[PDB]
Image (cartoon, coloured by chain):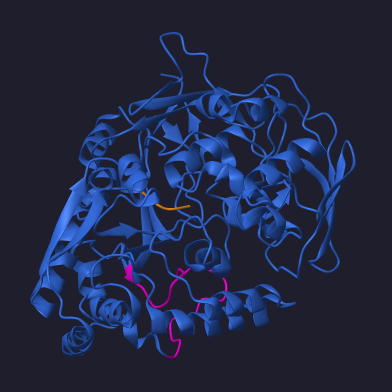
Chain colours: A blue, B orange
Amino acid sequence: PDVVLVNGGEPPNPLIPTGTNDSNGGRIIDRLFAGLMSYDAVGKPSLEVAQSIESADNVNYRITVKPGWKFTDGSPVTAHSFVDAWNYGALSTNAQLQQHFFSPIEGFDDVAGAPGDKSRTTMSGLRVVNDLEFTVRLKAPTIDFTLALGHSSFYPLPDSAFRDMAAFGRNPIGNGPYKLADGPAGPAWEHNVRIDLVPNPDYHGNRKPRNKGLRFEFYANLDTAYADLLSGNLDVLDTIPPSALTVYQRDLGDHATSGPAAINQTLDTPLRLPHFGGEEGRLRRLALSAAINRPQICQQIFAGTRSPARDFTARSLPGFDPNLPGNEVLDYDPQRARRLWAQADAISPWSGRYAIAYNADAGHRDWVDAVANSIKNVLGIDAVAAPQPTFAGFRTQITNRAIDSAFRAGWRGDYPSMIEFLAPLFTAGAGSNDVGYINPEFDAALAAAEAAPTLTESHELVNDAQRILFHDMPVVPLWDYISVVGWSSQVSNVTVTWNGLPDYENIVKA
Amino acid sequence: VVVA
């Protein structure tokens, strides 16, 4: 098998960049497209499809597109390929999960509040100048906007996409380093089984593949994946399962690497659930946080491969501070947890069951069982785990709001910015706000951080904003990741990126 | 992205 075999999972949603907010779809999307910038293994952006990106003020942007780029259907990548895709993502009528990434652009409010009788379908701040040039006017200085231009929300789309976006999402056509295979025995995307990609011969950008293709195998169980790794039937496994964390070093030797990654994990309890809204719900979320022993779970369940949360972002990000005032809400304190739960009971006495739903295909069983048992023992309530088989179905129930319990969540960074760990999850309208948290004061504080002229002041304002999150506990931050990645004896040049994923394009296979 |  010339192709590199790596682990993945069925995407919950069609393969439309602005419609993808999860890592299963994301790891495919990022192989199929090339954006204005591309990111290296440490998350630094470089010009890719853009010939230049100019802004002196973080408000006005002039973007020129390199000539000669095309999609795999032969059509050219133009300024329109970007502007039309961004307007599609921003328009509320299209219900794109990545809509919030367009929020800084002037005119976003015309298209995003709702479908509306607004009569406007495009953003006034986004203006084509010529076939290979467009300008962007932001509502306010936005410190991360340039950095974000390597993210999938901003990928260009071919003209055909807009005539039938459902068809596009089933069979995407991109401009990136790989393309969907022309499989010799069935479709490239075998739903719930695998996706096969081959190099795109048109592509001459910054991420040229060093291998002959990629096969993302959609494992139902990470123990199966680990067994395949040890037998050489899998080439790269980006998540060693809990059952192997005390053993992977002896099993794999120098074919496994570990390190902090900008990924976190949270316990999400929708504010719409019984006993979990209003001030009552805030007190109960604070109680849950005090009822969980993060150091102990990190040591025993994860064998030291998770680090207890100290904020709502991740230890490895620029500006992170593990000693923020008020972060004591993230310390284990059973007496405090019981006091807070009782104070919530003063509003309305608790009744029923507290269930933590999770996707069993990614090794969460041990920690969810431990957290549920900790809550049960500290607070004296009926707390249980509620496994579901697949990430795709689990996320679908979270997104459509069918899910009727608490559930695990967590963010893998898209670019290295604390703001990017907060805006998609906790601002009022964000598509990845799974719990219905709304606090206009937090959104305002975060906007102030985005408007800072320097990264230093911006980081200070981000952490100021996180004081509100310590008070509201919109979700319960658990820990951030020490990624552990293993690979077979048939591949080399395996680098783990800043956000825990293999650097797929650069893997080599003899 | 939301993580598996």
Q: Nearer the viewer, residue A252 or A422?
A: A422
Left or right: A355 with respect to A237?
A: left
Left or right: A327 with respect to A495?
A: left
Q: Position of residue A393 (x, y in %)?
A: 31, 41
Left or right: A356 with respect to A82?
A: left
Does residue A405 show up magenta in the picture?
Answer: no
- Residue at (36%, 70%) from the top-left corner? A475
Q: Which residues are magenta?
A: A307-325
Whether residue A20 is visible, yes or no, is: yes
Position above or below: A378 against A105: below
Q: Position of residue A27 (x, y in %)?
A: 49, 40
Q: Position of residue A462 (x, y in %)?
A: 57, 78
- Residue at (24%, 81%) from the top-left corner? A287
Whether residue A493 is visible, yes or no, is: no
Q: Quadrant of residue A284?
A: bottom left
Q: Main secondary structure of the magenta part?
A: loop
Spot the residue most to the right: A130
Does residue A317 show up magenta in the picture?
Answer: yes
- Residue at (59%, 52%) from the top-left corner? A99
Q: Position of residue A117 (x, y in %)?
A: 67, 51
Q: Quadrant of residue A478?
A: bottom left
Left or right: A203 with respect to A135?
A: left
Q: Quadrant of residue A161?
A: top right
- Residue at (59%, 42%) from the top-left corner? A94
